[PDB]
Amino acid sequence: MFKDGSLIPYLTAGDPDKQSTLNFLLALDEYAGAIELGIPFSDPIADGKTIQESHYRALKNGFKLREAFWIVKEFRRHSSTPIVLMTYYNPIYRAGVRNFLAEAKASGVDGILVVDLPVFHAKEFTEIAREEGIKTVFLAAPNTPDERLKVIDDMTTGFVYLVSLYGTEEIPKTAYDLLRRAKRICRNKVAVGFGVSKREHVVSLLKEGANGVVVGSALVKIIGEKGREATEFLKKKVEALLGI
Image (cartoon, rainbow, N blue to C red; front, side):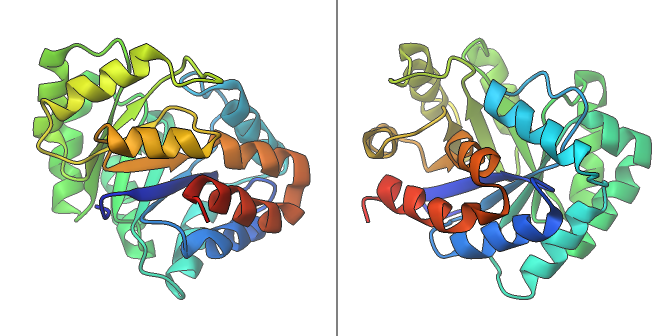
């Protein structure tokens, strides 16, 4: 969904408020090859400490599901940059799969990633996403075996998202191994979310085959610390990470 060598910012919708999120997105659009917009959830058990807290902040401050569509719709007035909606299954499921995807598409969403999509619903979900014109983005972690990477790659229409809970301040070997294994199996492009925080992490990861590098924790950390005034600092972090 994105150009090779793309830096893909991840932001939590509604952190601290939907307007600030829109402001951060626009300030970073010029450096992004694609963007991940996360829908806050009460139990984000698949995320790291940093991103879990942003989910808590968002919800406390009163984030509402469709405020995410607002952010996308408004962003779309100024940009065509690919947008991936990252969410937990619960919200989609509780609102009606097709209803959610149909609504997401209308706002401007290009792809969707369901962190905890039950394998039982895998098939049905992908079939509906396609019918609704939404590309699928599936996640894989260091404990994902080759046979599963393949199954994941065969269902993916957007790109394969490789994650690593390890954290760092070095990218663990288990992370690099996951990347190495994926590039040897995926026909789809892969993006990596290994918690980058330094320029060398970006260079390294792209040199090892990551088509794109996501930057989420690094940005969310600054937003938890600067609230609405995170914008300027976000722009600098991304530049540092981009070697500019």
